[PDB]
Length: 70
Length: 70
Image 1 (tube, chains in turn green, orange):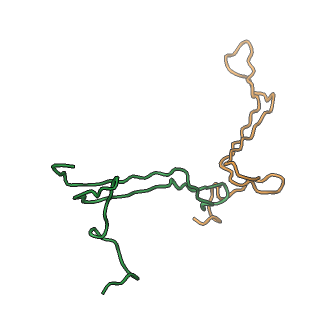
Image 2 (cartoon, rainbow over the protein chains, first blue to last red; image 1 turned 180 degrees about the horizontal axis):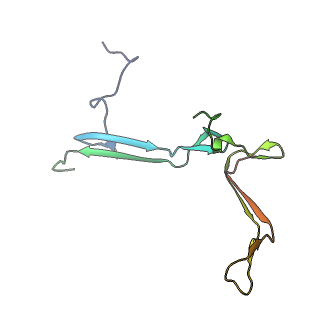
């Protein structure tokens, strides 16, 4: 039995590709992402009035076993 | 302590108003005041005999985040 209504990605389900070649023996990939969300405050209340996005940042980290070639 | 019970004013306990409308996004206000207080000296003592007020001056500075309107 194979159902689509629930499914999760897994290490076996996902290829990593660079320039149209799959990366062999990749052990992990970690993608991280940040928007710099800054809260707006003013005289008259302690509450945040608003949030603003100010600076996008992100990194991709890859661990791999060192092959003898490629 | 409850806001109704604090002994000290704090930024949330006060509002800034001009022409009967609250000034939004107010970050700070600084009020300064000078009296020109000058000491009088005379021959026979090294010490000021009295101080006198000469010229009142004062400035109020307001700083805000710039809104898209108002």
